[PDB]
Length: 400
Length: 49
Image (cartoon, rainbow over all chains, first blue to last red; front, side, top):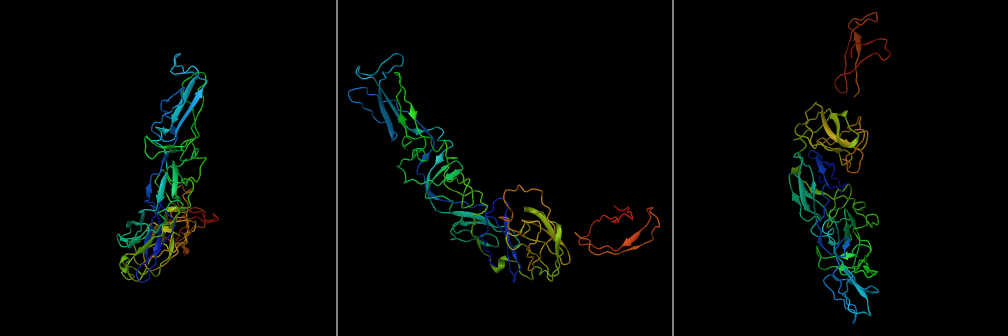
């Protein structure tokens, strides 16, 4: 009567199920968990990415105490070096003949590559989550409502009233703190902004793009510019945009107990083939077409016309229908066991009518609930040789 | 899918392997359509494709 389904996510080739009803004709669902998306309430904690030591010009004090005055960008590396007297054409600027100093100074500033192609941390909370889901319904055979994933607000679009969620499209495998580097979202904790994570994620930590301030524990180490040369060499640990895609933590575009893949995101959940959104529909008696205002199919028999073995649509099977009433006649197989493209089958008494479907097996022995009548549409399913369709129509290859 | 019932009897035949022998067949089938035929021994050689 009210076909709940926490059936595997599908997004690539919709899956189908059947509301059995004996008072009224059974009515189809196409439960398309196409968006398993998230709407976190979040906070940009820090961009990370490979640095650029766009050095401030060294505040060289050569004697009379060394003074290095700081300029914008917290975490300011400055190191005196002696035994080098500064030349640039043969020149000098140092102001002792008892000290030959070259004082190298370097701060971290965001790379220009940080602007475009970069890692991005987040403090991720559940927030005001939502997902949209198709239910084909009645004999209208389409309605795709979008409601909050937490139940909360039902919405009746077409015949069915459709409730999406609770939470199963409101969380990805994110932790509270996550760093993201590419497609791959990395469940990488840190104790808020203001912390140092050199040689990992948060080596650079800018809270603004095209930075003028950041926190850069990048393991920045100045070395001696030997032979009276004036330059600043920067020795620095690799970043969250120099690797961590094979020095990976938990690479979410390659792992997920949410059964999804993830991109460079404040956390959304792309392309889920399992991760089941628990779907709940409130379908009144009205939402069905009634038993005697539809056929009640009696004397039916099913045989293939030609099924296709593959969890993609194309399998067909005539059913030599014959009933005791006439009308419209919704059809569907019980669950994703056979996923039927035809939400509705036309029915005339003593005729024969092919419907469309998809199977996860070579024998199409799925019941089809033809307006208060099951029938096994057994026969022969000739595969399309080789299935390259991205996901199974069934929803997880649920067998007929 | 499977050819379900049928019975055959002459409508005057040949005593010869010349093609001229005919026989009506009260055919019936799981689904109506075409049905290629030939004797499965080839003792009757059938001109009907």
